[PDB]
Image (cartoon, one colour):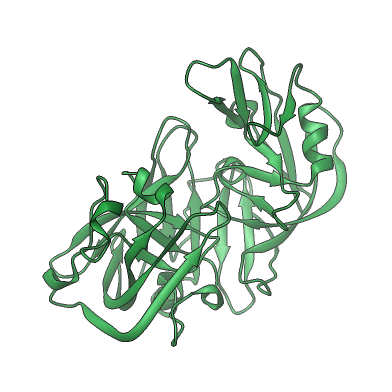
Length: 330
């Protein structure tokens, strides 16, 4: 089997992407944030504290003929941005882009933090990291990908995120029309439960490539590119008037600037992030200070190849017995 679903930016900045997901019988379609940096499929629901729901579509298990309480199971998760959610668990039928899993754990939120409530466009998360990170207790649950894997034509999914445009998540096949040149594959460590890999270096604009190992994670659920402070300083030093602002919480730059590209290495191959991808617009409405899309990972404890980086590539998440990542230009 295969599946193929379109993923759509939630706003004009590509702050996140949402993908429609069918849950239950008859189908309830929720727009979920596919997150290769976490491993829980959780939704706004009929159980969510009413004051914490503001415009989201909810899952109502009582209206699904295939929903079953997973008795005694609870979940609770905290993300890198400080947000959180928790609740109880149902099993139900879940379909993505025509690919169906029966018996998927659907984590129903009883509580969500303010950043979830305030984002009316995201109805929950669908985690695509390794199932070792899933938070369900006392019986850990599998991701949608892990449950689908054995049925897929190939044990893979791909992320093809758009810049200010829709893109695609495919399951079980590699669309050879969706990228240019060849795919370069690189090793993955699953020790921390992430799609963790090592980039071979970077370049800023038309500058020379610096060969250096940068360990980090491929994380579709993170907006920005978080890299070591040395790398990030070298990038922003090429932008007149850019500075790190402790009041704003990262590097800002004049909205009048033209940003240089940023290249990262994948083995001997190179992915180029155009400068425009690094502009996250005014820090507050009407400001002439703009927020940068490349930020320091200092204090986060890991480098993160978030959407800024991934949207410049066609990315293969290879879930074979020995997982690997693939990157192609597009």
